[PDB]
Image (cartoon, rainbow over all chains, first blue to last red; front, side, top):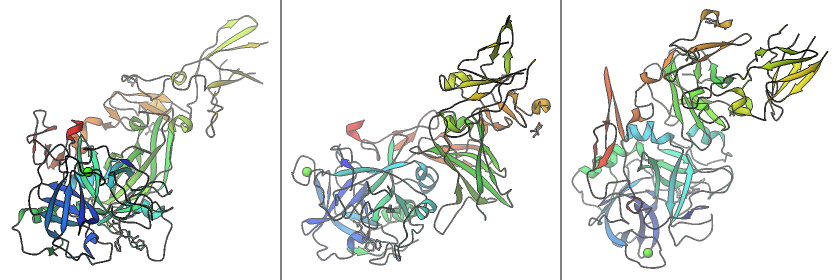
Length: 254
Length: 191
Length: 95
Ligand SMILES: *C[C@@](*)(O)[C@H](CCCNC(N)=[NH2+])NC(=O)[C@H](Cc1ccccc1)NC(=O)[C@H](N)Cc1ccccc1
Ligand SMILES: [Ca+2]
C-alpha cells in the first residue's frame, strides 16, 4: 500500500493475512467465521497446501499481541473461468478448517446484494484498500497494517485517463479501476486479495478485491480490482452448499 | 445506443440546467452530479428530455466545482455493457457555480434625486440559492466581490446598490475577480 | 416578459431575463418550469430509495427497504439495526 497510513488497530477488522510455509502470501477479506475472500492469482505458485494459514486480528507482523487468530485453510475455490497468470476473474473463496471467533478485532465485511453494489455503492466516491504489501513499487512490505482511501472510476474514465501500453490487459466487466494516475497513492504487490471496502449509511460493504496494476502508483495508471458484485451470487452458492473434497477447487462460473 | 454529446451548462443567477444532445431515438437518459471528492447523485431519471435542472444540487455549495454525466439506456433497460459492465455515458465540463454563473440582467429599482446630484439605486436581486428554504440576494452571495457600472445620457462605478453623479441610465452587475462571464448584461433603461 | 405566459408551474414564480426567464420553485419542486415533484421519484436508483441498506422497486406499489443478515428493519421501514453481536461491516472499537 503506497502512500497510505497505518490502519489504527481494530479498525480494519476484516483483514486476513495469508501465510504459507510461514511466509507472506496475500491478504483477504473475512465474509463470515469460516469464509474469506481473496484473489485467485495468490494461488498460482503454491506448493505446501498443507501449511496455508489464514491470520485474523493481526496488525503488527513484528510483534505478537492479544488478538491474532490463525486457522488452516481447508479449501481454496477459484472461478472456473480463471486462467493462471491472466487478470480476469481474480477472486477466491477460502473455507477455514474452523471458525474464527468474532471479537472487537475480528469482524466480517458485508458482502452486499448485487443491485445494491451496482446502483449504490459503485457511486460512493471513496473506499479503503488495505494490506501489508509493498510500500513503494519495488520497495519493502509493511509491518503495521496499511490503509488507503482511493476514488473509484467508471471504466470509460479509466480508459480515457490511462497512458496506453502494448499489452496492459483490458479492464473487463469483472474488473474496475480506482486510485490516482498522478503517482502518489495506490495498492501494491502482496496486498492482493485484500479489501476494497465502501462506507454506506454506517456499515462497510465489500465492493472490490485487490488484483493487478502496472507497477504501483505508476504515473497515468490506476489500481485494478475484481468487481465483487459480478460474483456475489456465485460466492453465496458456494457458501450455502455441501463441502466438496479438494484443497484447490475450480467451481463453475457464472 | 448512442452517447450524449455537447454537454453544456446554462446557468443564470444560480438556476443551472445542463443541456445536451441528441434528442432520444428509443433511448432514455439519467444525469449524475458530484463535486470532485463527493459521491455521484442521480437526477432526471430515465428522461427523454435533453435538459436537467441541477440547481438544487449545485446551490448546496456555490463555490465547489461540479462535474455531471449523462447515461444512455435503451428504453426499458437499464443495462449495460460490455465493453465492460456499466451503462453508456458521457461527461460534462467541470462547472463552478460561484465563478461561472451568468449574472442576471439587473433592474434599477430607485431613481429619486437630491437636486444636482442624482441617486440611482440598483435592486438587491434574489438568487436561486436557498437558506432555510428562502432565497439569498445577489449581494448576499457575492458581497465585496460584486460591483456596478453605470451609464447615462459616459460612465461611473460603485460597490453597493447606490450611485451619486453630476449634471437615461443602464447598469451592469460586474465581478472583476472573474476569469469568465465577468460582466452581466445591461439593465433596462430608465428616464 | 418572456414570463408573459407564466411558464413557472407548481406555484413557483417567474423572473424575466432578456431572451429568457427564470423560475424560482417552492421547496418541493425543481425543473426549468418547476415541472418536477421532488416527492415523486422514490425509486431505488435514486439515493437507495432512502433505504439504509437494501432496496426493492415494486411494480405499482411503494418500494421496500430490507437488510443484511444480522440486521432487521426498523419501524420507520428504512433503517436497520443489528440483531447480532458482531454484525458485519461495523467497527466495534468505533461503536
Ligand atoms: C496479487 C497482488 O498482490 C498484486 C497486486 C498489485 C496491484 N498493483 C496496483 N498498482 N494496484 N498483483 C500482482 O502481483 C499481479 C499478479 C498477476 C496477475 C495476473 C497476471 C499476472 C500476474 N501482477 C501485476 O499486477 C502485474 N503488473 C500485471 C501486469 C500489468 C501490466 C502489464 C502486464 C502485466
Ligand atoms: Ca501482531
